């Protein structure tokens, strides 16, 4: 689990969105595994606006942060789960590293701020849903 809180927005993995998230839906994209909901309290997280390909991610299954190199956001094939059939997930960034299904929502950060959140994993690869292109999160 995990979320990004910026302004009056809460950003979570779409497959983990709650009833309150859907009842206060702002925007969602199944092809990206992203959902943004509105909040009453103000959020103070900083979203990165960059092309970084290095950063650090939180892995709850190891209670550890790992430094990683990751690919630029792209369309990648993702095998079926109880949440989605087999499809291409867009705006996804891959890195070599550990993950478990419960690690979704862990934040990936660079010196500029929040890059994205853990969304996929398999075969020793971990994928992050990018949020750097969502310029509207900052107003
Ligand atoms: C081994 C492993 N690590 C993780 C993070 C996973 C879970 C995973 O990849 N999923 C399941 C939830 C929906 C995801 C999606 N975006 O389509 C796919 N598995
Ligand atoms: Zn950066």
Image: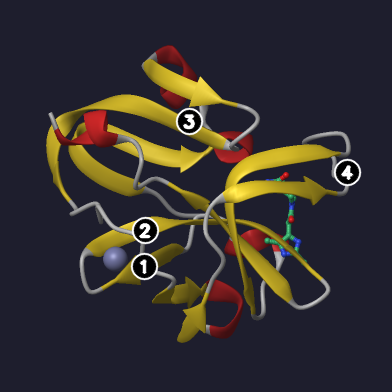
> Do callouts 4 and 1 mark residues in contact (Cβ within 8 Å)?
no
Q: Position of residue 29 (x, y in %)?
A: 55, 26
Residue drawn at (19%, 53%) of the image: 45
Q: Secondary structure at mark 4?
A: loop
Determine whether the beta carbon of the residue marked 1 sits less than 8 angstroms from the nearest atom of ligand 2: yes
> In what quadrant of the picture does the C terminus appear?
top left
Mark 4 neighbour class, 10 Å CA radius: few under 14, some 14 to 19, many 20 or more: few
1 or 2: tag closer to the N-terminus? 1
4 or 1: tag closer to the N-terminus? 1
Mark 2 neighbour class, 10 Å CA radius: few under 14, some 14 to 19, many 20 or more: many
Q: Secondary structure at mark 3?
A: strand
Determine whether the beta carbon of the residue marked 2 sits less than 8 angstroms from the nearest atom of ligand 2: yes
Q: Name the residue beneath numbered marker 4.
A: 80
Mark 3 neighbour class, 10 Å CA radius: few under 14, some 14 to 19, many 20 or more: many
Mark 1 neighbour class, 10 Å CA radius: few under 14, some 14 to 19, many 20 or more: some
Q: Name the residue beneath numbered marker 3.
A: 35
Give the image quadrant in which the ligand numbered 2 is located.
bottom left
Residue toward you, 46 or 41:
46
Q: Is residue 64 visible?
A: no
4 or 2: tag closer to the N-terminus? 4
Residue toward you, 71 or 136:
71
Q: Name the residue beneath numbered marker 1.
A: 52
Q: Position of residue 120 (x, y in %)?
A: 68, 56
Q: Name the residue beneath numbered marker 2.
A: 115
Q: Secondary structure at mark 2?
A: strand
How is colour applied across the structure in the image? secondary structure
- Mark 4 vs mark 1, foreground winner is 1
2 or 3: tag closer to the N-terminus? 3
Residue drawn at (57%, 84%) of the image: 62
- In-image side of 126 versus 6 (left or right): right
């Amino acid at each position: 689990s995990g979320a990004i809180y910026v302004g009056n927005y809460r950003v979570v993995n779409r497959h983990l969105a709650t009833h309150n998230d859907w009842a206060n839906l702002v925007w969602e994209d199944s092809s990206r595994d992203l959902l943004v909901s509105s909040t009453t309290a103000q959020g103070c997280d900083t979203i990165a606006r960059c092309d970084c390909q290095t950063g650090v991610y939180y892995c709850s299954s190891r209670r550890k942060h790992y430094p990683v190199s990751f690919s630029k956001p792209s369309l990648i094939f993702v095998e079926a789960s109880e949440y989605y059939p087999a499809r291409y997930q867009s705006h996804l960034m891959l890195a070599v590293g550990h993950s478990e299904p419960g690690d979704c929502g862990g934040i990936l950060r660079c010196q500029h701020g929040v890059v994205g959140i853990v969304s996929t994993g398999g075969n020793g690869l971990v994928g992050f849903a990018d949020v750097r292109d969502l310029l509207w999160l900052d107003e």
